[PDB]
Image (spheres, rainbow, N blue to C red):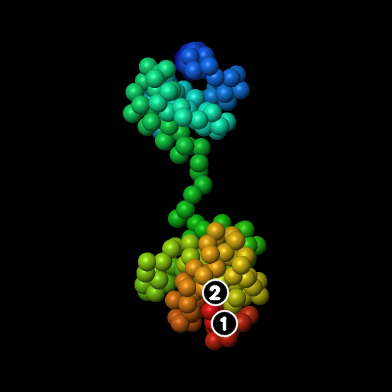
Amino acid sequence: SSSDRAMMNAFKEITTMADRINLPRNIVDRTNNLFKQVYEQKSLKGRANDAIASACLYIACRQEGVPRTFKEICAVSRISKKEIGRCFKLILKALETSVDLGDFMSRFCSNLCLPKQVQMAATHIARKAVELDLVPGRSPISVAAAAIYMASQASAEKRTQKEIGDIAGVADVTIRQSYRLIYPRAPDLFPTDFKFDTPVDKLPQL
């Protein structure tokens, strides 16, 4: 097959490159698997198979802790460091469909075991806080942490500064600080319909 001949040739290239830099079979096996996985997918269309394989070899190396390869790989490859590099970044994008946007709200609340309504209110708070410029020059993760703390403390599913800090990967002081900024406008920040377990007035002062 035209798709299979491309693969047979790419695996041939992977092996001839791997022996050229004395790499073990596990590295070769990982590279082939990684190649099959990515070589035909959106971004890598039009991109040379030779370059895809080279970038896949570097990835497999990085992954299994064989270091200081980037320059060494491009040397054993017939492709430029520029194309191998471009291929490499595209492959990471393909292998990593996890990152940051309230993307954090979705993640942190799942990590904190928080209801849809709590998550929704905390997202609403965090978003409105930005809209009203209550939190300028503030880490969006510190804002989200404070928004989660505020919403969770107003709901039955109350969460502590410590645990929010643990999940957000932020220091407790940062949550406190960001919370201190949104605390004054808390009644305006909550969604209208929100059903309070603890009234907006009797919310914790930090």
Q: Extreme front residue here?
A: 68
Q: Number of numbered discs present?
A: 2
First along the sequence among labels 1 and 2: 2
| Residue at the (44%, 67%) spot, across then down | 127
Residue 37 visible in the displayed image: no
Q: Residue at x 62, y 58 (%)?
A: 111
Q: Is residue 196 left or right of residue 140?
A: right
- Name which residue type carries label 1: Leu
Q: Kindly identify the amino acid type of the residue bearing the numbered disc 2.
A: Met
The residue identified by callout 1 is 203
Q: Residues within 10 Å of mark 2 (few under 14, many from 20)?
A: many
Tag of residue 150 = 2
Q: Are marks 1 and 2 in contact (CB under 8 Å)?
A: yes
Q: Where in the figure is residue 201, as x and y percent of width and height?
A: 54, 86
What's the mark number on residue 110? none
- Residue 86 vs 107, above or below: the answer is above
Q: Is residue 87 above or below residue 50?
A: below
